[PDB]
């Protein structure tokens, strides 16, 4: 029918398609017609995902995952994205579907994240047929989700006043120490900026952002806790009451 090279197409939707070859006269009437049925089925995609770390996960450590993608008989490059509860990675990452059948799913490397907060966290791995680089966003080939709990790290406070009863119009030294429920991992030093409000001024920051500004402001101090240590350095605020 032509001397041109073969033409390649990828079907957007699933179902049954009718590759149709037609012969047209001058009046665009069908003379001869040939139909080839193409079955576009997106099933048969297996997505495995699990967490490597098995001990009670803390917010200090980094939780890593092992993930893989497999198809029954299709060896075609797909795209994958990962969501840790905050959204999906903006560039879809290409995956080569070298292995098929039931031998071994193709693995996905460098899957890890650090969870700032605690509680129940879920990780969802999704695979799409087409890259989302452009306006094209192919059908979601498959998805999976694994949920787990992470124990948050709680902070306890020890407080004292250098004079136990601050004399009116006399300076008093508030001393503060911070205890961490879990020892900080080695190589990680924690610098926490703290702001204190005494009853002398009579006005306290009623807003969280105001407290943050006070901590980062002049009337705030910094407590440094060294790696592999529970306690913190003593923090001393001098305040005068009238």
Image (cartoon, rainbow, N blue to C red):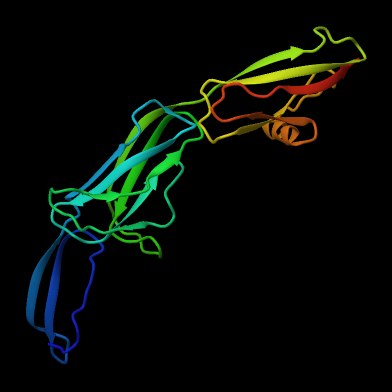
Residue 83, given in percent of the width and then of the height, sits at: 40, 44
Tell which residue pokes out farthest to the top in this image.
165
The residue closer to the viewer here, 78 or 240, is 240
Q: Quadrant of residue 202?
A: top right
Residue beneath the point at 44% across and 55% down = 90
Residue beneath the point at 69% across and 34% down = 212
The residue closer to the viewer here, 114 or 118, is 114
Q: Is residue 217 left or right of residue 41?
A: right
Q: Quadrant of residue 149?
A: top left
Q: For residue 202, say whether it is visible.
A: no
The residue closer to the viewer here, 164 or 214, is 164
Residue 62, given in percent of the width and then of the height, sits at: 44, 37
Residue 211, given in percent of the width and then of the height, sits at: 71, 31
Residue beneath the point at 13% across and 56% down = 73
Note whether 42 is above or below 116 in the view shown: below
Looking at the rendering, in which quadrant would you find the N terminus? bottom left
The residue closer to the viewer here, 103 or 185, is 185
- How many numbered marks appear? 0
Note whether 122 is above or below 92 in the view shown: above
Q: Quadrant of residue 13?
A: bottom left
Q: For residue 222, say whether it is visible.
A: yes
Residue beneath the point at 12% across and 52% down = 101
């Amino acid at each position: 029918v032509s001397s041109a090279a073969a033409s390649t197409f990828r079907y957007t939707s699933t179902g049954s398609k009718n590759a149709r070859l037609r012969l047209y006269d001058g009046a665009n009437n069908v003379i001869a017609e040939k139909i080839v049925v193409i079955t576009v089925s997106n099933a048969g995609y297996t997505l495995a995902l699990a967490k490597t770390t098995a001990d009670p996960v803390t917010t200090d450590d980094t939780i890593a995952f092992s993930a893989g993608a497999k198809h029954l008989s299709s060896t075609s490059q797909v795209w994958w994205t990962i969501d840790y509860g905050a959204g999906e990675s903006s560039p879809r990452t290409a995956l080569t579907m070298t292995n098929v059948g039931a031998a071994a799913p193709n693995a996905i490397a460098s899957l890890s994240n650090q969870y700032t907060s605690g509680g129940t966290k879920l990780a969802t791995l999704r695979i799409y047929d087409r890259d989302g680089v452009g306006a094209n966003t192919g059908l979601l080939l498959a998805s999976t989700t694994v949920t787990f709990t992470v124990t948050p790290v709680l902070y306890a406070l020890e407080s004292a006043v250098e004079p136990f009863s601050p004399i009116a119009t006399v300076a008093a030294k508030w001393s503060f120490r911070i205890q961490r429920s879990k020892a900080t991992p080695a190589g990680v030093t924690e610098s926490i900026k703290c702001a204190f409000f005494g009853a002398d001024t009579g006005t306290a920051p009623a807003d969280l952002a105001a407290w943050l500004t006070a901590a980062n402001g002049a009337g705030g101090l910094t407590a440094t806790i060294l790696p592999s240590s529970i306690p913190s350095d003593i923090i001393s605020f001098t305040r005068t009451y009238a």
